[PDB]
Image: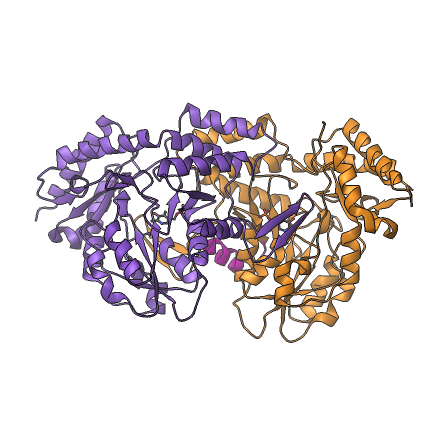
Chain colours: A orange, B purple
């Protein structure tokens, strides 16, 4: 064999050490470490508040449910069809109707194609930093200010990524990050909502934990519902430990990407996105875009790659194509999204991928594409 | 000092070892160990299906949401006011209106006071095994069969507890368990829904994880929404390890309880519930009930206890007393619930409490009560 998944977790002696001491403690959850992890996120991102969750999908639900109250008259939210289905499933769960915008070459939501989709039902815009590349923040901030819309950012891919030399996380009303096993850094399962809005932070904090407010050690008060989406102490210690070396892990991915770039440069088969970056990316993904000619035999290419141990993946199937979304709003397919979908392949890319591996992978990808003459 | 919390987690060399090997794995989530943990639950409980979640509150949401589809005409569910607010908050989140039944001496829902609360809107009955003592299963099973009602059980307290020499978990349409830090066994945060209904297991399974159905390694299908309430591999390993010694841990609590029983026997201040058991209990709590005379100075008693290092707690404030529930349905106070609330104190009780400690605690409790003459 010799099989490379598209991403994998990268833990070290430190991470493990960090988890041990927690197991020695009487305080396994709702303890000092999640608070520490939250503060460390704040300093890393330069934002004013941070909340950690069991998953980013819980984070998303919490944000959608709490950034404003729900009004049946302001029930539309614009977002991208190119993202993990979770971005939209949580919109549904919060009563909102997703309105799918066109995307651009780089997989990011098309900021120029947003305004025509706004009507008096439009409440918010939910962008996704695809592969860790920050969307056109300045452009969207303004569109929303102009139309009194809330700017929400699913930045699951992008912890560490920058826009105009400023870290992603601060730009939206709130931003979501993910610490799933295979994201930039991990807590096995995990997520976070950061924001500069204290009131929002507070509402979310409660929603995350039963809506319980304290009085004394013996009694509480509940003025509104909440769940249990808390991140426990074991995972928080892991997160803290992972975050400390976040820039290091990002750079490893960056170097892997540069190696891909050297070898793919000017190839006749596909176009890699990484070279086109203007700001630092978390490099959560290393996507390549096939030329139109290869579309109709994509499946065979993926299988060919998999036969070489390159467990490639596609991000993402346009969300509106899922049976549930068809069922609910027969959504007209979007040329930009459909094209990107058929074209995109994410190659193996994570902090533990060494020089030798990248080169073997990069050459196998080329050998594969060329085998399918014209 | 020398402070005893009312419960605490009990990990050992095994537990830790178990967590380590997972940290050495490339598979930190959605892996072999949660499946293993799920099977181990099935054998322990003798049920046919088990699903593990990030928390019991997520488990509860998932059950409530999926045991049937929601119909505005069958929107009422009967449950107890004596339980953790989570039991009811998730009912609200699933569109249901909680209908609060009276309880009995032992804190359990009064099976004799249930029938009169049923009308053509009633959909289900949600019982709680208070302190790990099984409710009157036979009686409820029948009431539901008779009125075509779904029997749901919040058995968070009761993993290991028995009813008529059969383990709790099998008796309802489904049952929820919790592995929060201080429950019978722990995964730091964690929960489970067990059931003998495959279709229900399947719907819940999907709801737990984005509603994603597989096609090949490259594509999925989504016919209905789902979240991320998955339990990761680290916690699953912990759960597995903990479950192996579950009966051992339960017996440790049993012994602690028996020691309390010896010393409290015939005391003139309060009545402990443990002696009154008819079946094995998980002994998640060791509750004592004060006589009416002490009610009006409960607060001072709790503080007095706390000054002695006995960090006692009350389970539970009647749910309908929470500002949110008052707000939504000005619920008339129930004498049984109100009485139990004012009376109940949970004393320290967990697998790591040794003979010496229990005796010191037991005598301190007595000293405390007697200090408040008449
Ligand atoms: C995977 C992902 C999420 C889901 O978050 P989890 O941590 O897996 O719960 C949300 N949005 C995007 C864009 C994702 O990549
Ligand atoms: C604690 C508890 C829950 C909530 O479970 P978590 O694991 O904390 O999410 C639900 N019901 C009862 C009876 C509980 O005691």
Residue at left 70%, top 57%? A318
x and y, in percent, of residue B135 in the image = 25, 49
Q: Is residue B69 left or right of residue B110?
A: right
Magenta span: A195-208
Residue at left 44%, top 65%? B70
Residue at left 68%, top 59%? A321
Q: What's the magenta bit mostly, secondary-structure-wise?
A: helix
Along the viewing direction, whichever of A167 and A354 lies nearer the viewer? A354
Check the image and report above or below for B295 versus A123: above
Check the image and report above or below for A145 versus B41: below
Along the viewing direction, whichever of B220 and A283 lies nearer the viewer? B220
User: Would you identify the image quadrant in which residue A332 lies?
Assistant: bottom right
x and y, in percent, of residue A263 in the image = 87, 35
Q: Visible in this render: residue A153?
A: yes
User: Would you identify the image quadrant in which residue A148 lies?
Assistant: bottom right
Residue at left 26%, top 46%? B134
Residue B283 lies in the magenta stretch: no
Q: Visible in this render: residue A30?
A: no
Check the image and report above or below for A360 versus A372: above
């Amino acid at each position: 064999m010799k099989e490379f998944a598209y991403s994998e977790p990268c833990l070290d002696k430190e991470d493990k050490k960090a988890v041990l001491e927690v197991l020695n403690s009487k305080q396994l959850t709702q303890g000092k470490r999640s608070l520490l992890f939250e503060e460390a996120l704040c300093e890393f991102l330069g934002v004013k508040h941070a909340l950690v969750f069991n998953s980013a999908t819980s984070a998303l639900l919490t944000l959608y449910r709490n950034f404003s109250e729900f009004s049946a008259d302001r029930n539309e939210i614009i977002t991208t069809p190119i993202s993990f289905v979770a971005t939209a499933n949580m919109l549904l769960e919060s009563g909102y109707t997703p309105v799918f915008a066109g995307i651009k070459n780089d997989g990011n939501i098309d900021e120029l194609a947003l305004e025509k989709l706004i009507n008096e039902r439009t409440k918010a815009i939910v962008s996704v930093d695809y592969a860790g590349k920050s969307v056109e923040v300045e452009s969207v901030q303004k569109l929303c200010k102009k139309h009194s819309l809330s700017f929400l950012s699913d930045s699951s891919h992008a912890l560490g990524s920058e826009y105009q030399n400023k870290k992603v996380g601060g730009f939206a009303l709130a931003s979501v990050f993910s610490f799933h096993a295979i994201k930039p850094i991990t807590t096995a399962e995990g997520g976070a909502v950061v924001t500069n809005d204290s009131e929002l932070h507070e509402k979310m904090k409660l929603f995350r934990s039963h809506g319980m407010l304290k009085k004394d050690f013996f009694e509480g008060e509940v003025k509104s519902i909440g769940h249990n989406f808390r991140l426990n102490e074991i995972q928080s210690a892991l997160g803290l430990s992972q975050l400390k070396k976040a820039p290091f892990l990002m750079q490893k991915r960056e170097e892997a990407a540069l190696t891909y770039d050297r070898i793919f440069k000017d190839n006749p088969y596909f176009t890699p996105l990484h070279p086109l970056l203007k700001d630092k990316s978390s490099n959560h993904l290393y996507p390549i875009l096939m030329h139109q000619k290869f579309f109709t035999c994509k499946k065979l290419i993926l299988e060919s790659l998999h036969k070489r141990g390159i467990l490639a993946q596609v991000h993402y199937k346009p969300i509106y194509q899922y049976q549930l979304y068809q069922q609910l709003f027969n959504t007209a397919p979007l040329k930009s999204a459909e094209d990107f979908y058929h074209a995109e392949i994410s190659l193996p890319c994570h902090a533990n991928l060494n020089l030798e591996s990248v080169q073997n992978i990069a050459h196998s990808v080329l050998k594969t594409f060329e085998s399918f003459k014209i």
